[PDB]
Image (cartoon, rainbow, N blue to C red; front, side, top):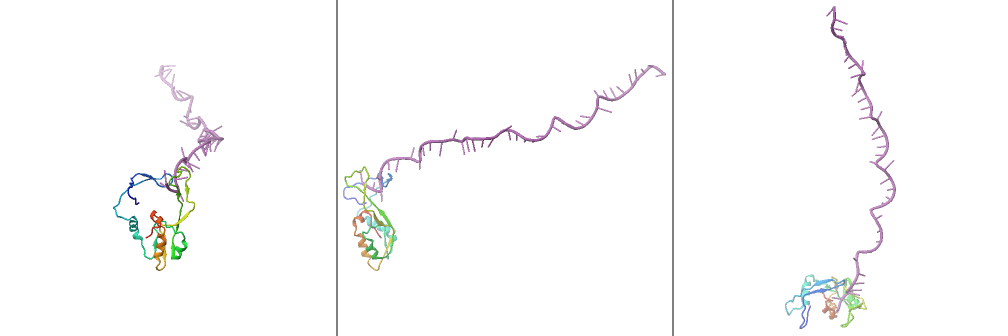
Length: 141
RNA sequence: AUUAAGACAUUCGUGAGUGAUUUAUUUCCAUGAAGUGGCGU
């Protein structure tokens, strides 16, 4: 996680997932001037193959037709996404509002075998959604 | 504020109903209430 300016994150006991699933945080501050994306890609370096793109985190593309046109083979799978949408001042005591649209992402471990060249085209299509990239989606090696 | 929060695998339920420790088996087999006279020559 990257926190801007004055923001302290203390280790505590947290809730993550349904049925009040309980977890323990350990907050460790790594050295400064570091890029977390570069750290994740360094971790994923050992799975790199130059003839294909490896999907490491759930990847979303608005239209799969262009992606399929850009590669010869899509040895891929699909996962489901639906977010609980809450405003900054919401009820928080009641049935939460969920995303009215159910979204399909590319499963991690999927591989895209692009044509000759055009790797930059697929990469540009994937990184066109920078909001998802910041959150942790659409990460590849 | 995170496909989230709330939710006892719980309620009712006799290990109970029928059942003879009974049937078959001679306290029986063998066995002498018997033995001997004595003295007075």
